[PDB]
Image (cartoon, rainbow, N blue to C red; front, side, top):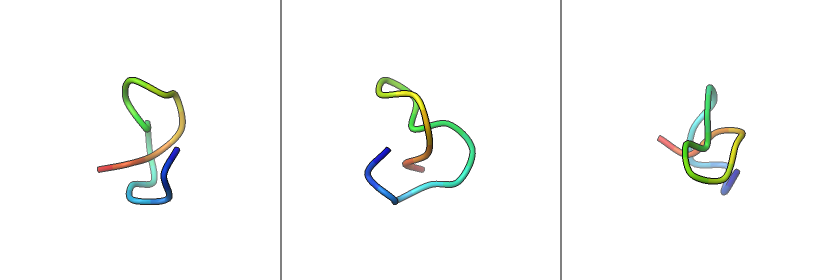
Length: 17
């Protein structure tokens, strides 16, 4: 969710590799 990923922010729910 910090715009560092593109599939699953993981702990936040969105994207943050």
